Amino acid sequence: GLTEEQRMMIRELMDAQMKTFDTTFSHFKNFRLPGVVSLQLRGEDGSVWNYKPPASLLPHMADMSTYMFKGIISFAKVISYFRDLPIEDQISLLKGAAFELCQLRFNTVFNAETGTWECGRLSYCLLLEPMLKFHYMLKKLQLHEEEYVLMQAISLFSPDRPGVLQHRVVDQLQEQFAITLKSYIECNRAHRFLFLKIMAMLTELRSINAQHTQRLLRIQDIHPFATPLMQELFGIT
Amino acid sequence: GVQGLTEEQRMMIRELMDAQMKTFDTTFSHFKNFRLPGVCSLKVSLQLRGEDGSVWNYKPPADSGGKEIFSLLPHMADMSTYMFKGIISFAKVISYFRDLPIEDQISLLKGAAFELCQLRFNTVFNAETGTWECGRLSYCLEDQQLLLEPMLKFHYMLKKLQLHEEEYVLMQAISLFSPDRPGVLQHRVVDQLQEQFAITLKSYIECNRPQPAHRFLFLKIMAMLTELRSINAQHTQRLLRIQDIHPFATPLMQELF
Amino acid sequence: SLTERHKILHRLLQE
Amino acid sequence: SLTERHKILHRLLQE
Ligand SMILES: COc1cc(OC)c(-n2nnc(S(=O)(=O)c3ccc(C(C)(C)C)cc3)c2C)cc1C
Ligand SMILES: COc1cc(OC)c(-n2nnc(S(=O)(=O)c3ccc(C(C)(C)C)cc3)c2C)cc1C
Image (tube, chains in turn cyan, purple, yellow, red):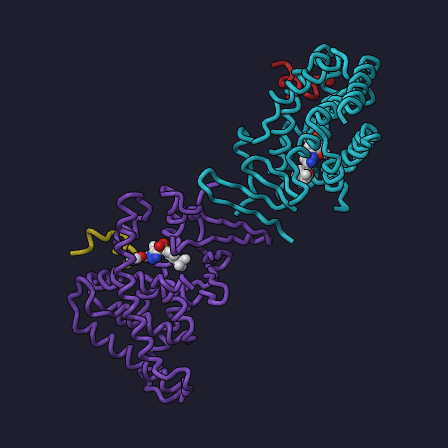
C-alpha cells in the first residue's frame, strides 16, 4: 500500500480539488455570447438555446477559460507546498501550467460517447486536431479522480518553466508527486504502463499548449478577444 | 383570358399589388430589437440565422404546469406588432380606405388586423416543412393532430389552394372592407366596396384559372375568409385570458384588443 | 369617438 | 518585474 505521507498528499490534493472545482459550473455567470464547436444552453425552465457556428465564439471561450483559470489559481493556493514557494515562482508555475490544468479539468467533464464537454447548463459539441485527440486518448485511460489530481500536481510543479528560481525544490516536489502516482497505480490497479502513458499525455499536452498559444497570439493581434487575466498569462500588453 | 377584366378591375388589382409591394417586407429586413426568450398545440421553435452564417435555435419548454408555457409570447407580440404596422400602411395607401372617415378606418383596422396578418403569414408558410420563413427568422412546428387546431388547419388548407399574389391581395381587401365590424358608420359604402373587390376576384379567377384543380376556387376562398373571421374570435378570446394573468401585449396590441 | 382610446392607431393613420 | 507584469495574478494570489 501507500505510506502515511503519500496518503496525506493525495488527501490534500483531493481536498483542494473539491474546494476549487465547481463541476456543475453553477457560478459561471455573465459570460459573453455570440450575437443574434456548437454551444448549448439549458435554462432552469426546460428551454434549450443552441448556437451553430458558421461553415466569434472566442469572447465566450475566453470567459470560460478565465473562469477555469481562476479555479486553478485557487487550487494551487490551497496546496501547502505551493504556498511555501516564493511569490515569483508561484506566478511562473501558474503561467506555465494554466493551459494544461484547464484541459485536464475539462477532460473530466468530456463525454467521449457524444463528443461533448458537459459544463453544467452549458455544453460544447463538435479528431486529427491534436486537442480533440488528447481528450479522446486521455478519456480512454479511465483515470480516477486521484490520478487526475496527481497529474495536475505533476504539471504544476514543473521545474523547467520559463522563470523558476527554486528549480531544485520544485524538481523534488514534482518527483514525490510522481512517485505517489506510481505507487497509487501499483496499489490500486495489466495497467503495467499506465504511469508512463500518463506522462506521455502530459508531454503531448505540453506540445499542444505551444501550438495553441502561437495560434491565439496571432488571432489576438488582429482581433483582440482576451480577458485581462489572459493577457497577463500570454505576456500581452 | 388575362384582358377579360374591365379597365377598372385592372387598375384595382394594380393599386392593391403595388400597395402590397410597398408595405410588405417579405425578407423582414427591418424587424429589429424584438424580445427573445431569455438565456401548447401552437408551440413553435424559433431559429435565427446571423448575417455571418451562424444559427441560434430556441426549443421551447415542455408543459410543466405554467409560468413558462408562454415563454415566446413577448416575441410573438413584437412580431405581430411589426406585421400590423405593415397592415396599417397597406390600408393607408388604398384610395378607397383613405376616403373613409377616420373612425371607420380605425374600426376596420381593429376588426381585420388579425386576419390580414394571418394572410400575409400564409405567404411565407412552407407546408412541406411546417415552417414560416420570415427572413433571417423561422418558426417551426414541433412533432396530423396539428390539424385539430383551426389556425394550423387554415394555414395548411390555404396553402393547398396555391393562390397567386393577386388573389392574396384581393382576399386582404375583402377582409379589410367588411361592412359588419363593431363600430362602422359608413356601412353602406363599405358594403359596396367589399362587393366590387369580390367581383374582381371572381373575374380574376375566371380570366386566369381554367383547370379542374381550381373548380370552385372563388367560393373556397370566401369560405376560408369566413372561417378566418371565426378563428379570430376564438384567438382573441384566448389572448385576452392570457393577457389578464401574464401581461405581454405591446401598446399597439392593447389598443387593438 | 374611438380616437381617444386608440392614440397610436390615430397617430399611425395621420402619418 | 515578474510581479509587476502580472498584477492581477499577484492580486489573486495574495487573497
Ligand atoms: C495561458 O492560459 C491559457 C491558454 C490557453 O490557450 C493556449 C487557453 N485556452 N485554451 N484553449 C482555449 S480555446 O481556443 O478558447 C478552446 C476552449 C475550449 C475548447 C474545447 C471545449 C476543448 C473544444 C477548445 C478551444 C483557450 C483560450 C486557456 C488558458 C487559461
Ligand atoms: C387584432 O390584432 C391582433 C390579434 C391577434 O390575435 C387574435 C394577433 N395574433 N395572432 N396570433 C398571435 S400569436 O399567438 O402571438 C401567434 C402568432 C403567429 C403564430 C405562428 C407561428 C405564425 C403560427 C403563432 C402564434 C397574435 C398575437 C395579432 C394581432 C396583431
